[PDB]
Image: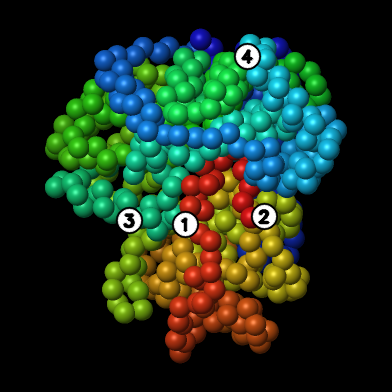
Amino acid sequence: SMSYSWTGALITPCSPEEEKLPINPLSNSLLRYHNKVYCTTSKSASLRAKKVTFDRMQVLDAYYDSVLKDIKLAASKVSARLLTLEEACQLTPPHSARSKYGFGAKEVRSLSGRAVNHIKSVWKDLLEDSQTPIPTTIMAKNEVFCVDKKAARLIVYPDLGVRVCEKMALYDVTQKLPQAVMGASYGFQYSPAQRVEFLLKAWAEKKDPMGFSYDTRCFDSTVTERDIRTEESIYQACSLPEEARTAIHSLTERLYVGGPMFNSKGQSCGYRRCRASGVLTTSMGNTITCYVKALAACKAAGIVAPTMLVCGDDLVVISESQGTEEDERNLRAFTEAMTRYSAPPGDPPRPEYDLELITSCSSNVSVALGPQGRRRYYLTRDPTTPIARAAWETVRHSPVNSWLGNIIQYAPTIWVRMVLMTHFFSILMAQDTLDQNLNFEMYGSVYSVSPLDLPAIIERLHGLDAFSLHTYTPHELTRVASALRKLGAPPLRAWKSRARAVRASLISRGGRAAVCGRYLFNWAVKTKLKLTPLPEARLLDLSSWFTVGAGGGDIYHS
């Protein structure tokens, strides 16, 4: 019942790691307190290992049984197909960890003979062997944060050849199952604006709304072998081809329920009996399992008219308040139920009665005014981590960055518009690489776009309002100002001074650059420009852009 067992071998790096932000003028113009920005490395891997290693005691009840029964029935409405090898390969990100069998992501995406022939044998083996555990590699993730340090997160994943096979057997399922059994509660199907709409709607439909977010301590580690086998039974409730059923059972028994882990040096590192952090089913599995336990927990605790929003292990519940004292009582009961289901809390949940203060996936809804003086709602978050990461990525190029993802996801926020856009467009112009497509992650998934196409992307995802919001809330302004001073970054008024110059340079360039200048920086001048709908905004193939990401899991798009 232990999440992990260890041999004693260390979790090793695949190359030297840098832990402190370098002193560079480009990064320094964004933030001066470089000593506050750090990156997690292999050095803290042992501390993390101890944190995620514990015994899981799970006891289910009638409430859980009832919800699961309902879920399986809903799953029967799903029909899915096996993805072709070619389709599976095209979903592989270009910088995906290479195989130990002689090929990398490049050969996969290009369908090289070597890659194709190996993948084929892996598939055949899955069909004839449903027992032999599949080996995985454990590594310490390198992530950037601002002090006030975190231990590195651990990632466990199978060989490239197996990752392609997972797509063939389950990608189609990840695209339909969550919605089928969860409906509107499935978070990954929404763009930021849709998430906002959902939360506002849920809040408004309650006579006396109360919300709370539940933080499960090390969710992946709380997932039991039984939980994972239950996930498979839910997958099998779908209408699937026999060959897929065989592959899915094999992957479950040989990979998902657990298996041996090796470090980068090839040494046996340990054995896993919980969720693998780096498999295709990580997000979908966490989402469904979190949903089942939470819905059952709500019923057992007496939560009234709960409306849930589930994103992997992230959970937010908005319901009818039963009074302050009752609410706190019900939340404790909820926690007790979640705990019995093997999902104890990291930080005890507390009832919240102001929507702007409720955090879902580190984000929250806030309000501002549009060009006509009307209230407009949008999604935002504390900008500390995004700015710290933007600084690191300015001096250390990452094949898959996070800043472009933050700019897209939080385009209407005051921090993206005044700080990130100003900073990156200045650097891109200086580098003269404005039109170059860049890979970035969003919702744990990998995407690729050109910053020159940002205005079209933003208008399509957030609307023209995204270029004209003003009069943000005191909470938002205070939070952004505090983040900047904490990082030693220039204040917003200085970013405004800089933006005027960036805007002018962009416009001087004409073409798409000028469009970026006129639309993205209209806020920087007192004499505002018109700003009409962009034609290319309609020619955009966005709609399920987030659904196709199905959370994360080594998935790539365009």
Q: Earlier in the sequence, mark 4 or mark 2?
A: 4
Q: Earlier in the sequence, mark 3 or mark 2?
A: 3
Identify residue type, mark 2. Asn
Please name the residue that numbered disc 3 is placed on.
Answer: 197
Label 2 residue SS: strand
Which numbered mark, 1 or 3, is in the foreground of this view?
1
Which x, y percent locates residue 318? 26, 42
| Circle 4 crowding by C-alpha within 10 Å: few under 14, some 14–19, many from 20 | some
Position of 485 relative to 164 (above/below): below
At 24% from the left and 49% from the top, the residue drawn is: 203
Q: How many marks?
A: 4
Dot label at residue 130: 4
| Circle 2 crowding by C-alpha within 10 Å: few under 14, some 14–19, many from 20 | many
Please name the residue that numbered disc 2 is placed on.
Answer: 439
Distance from the alpha carbon under mark 1 to that under mark 3: 15 Å
Q: Earlier in the sequence, mark 3 or mark 4?
A: 4
| Circle 3 crowding by C-alpha within 10 Å: few under 14, some 14–19, many from 20 | some
Which numbered mark, 3 or 4, is in the foreground of this view?
4
Q: Check whether the beta carbons of the residues at disc 3 and disc 4 lie within 8 A of each other.
A: no
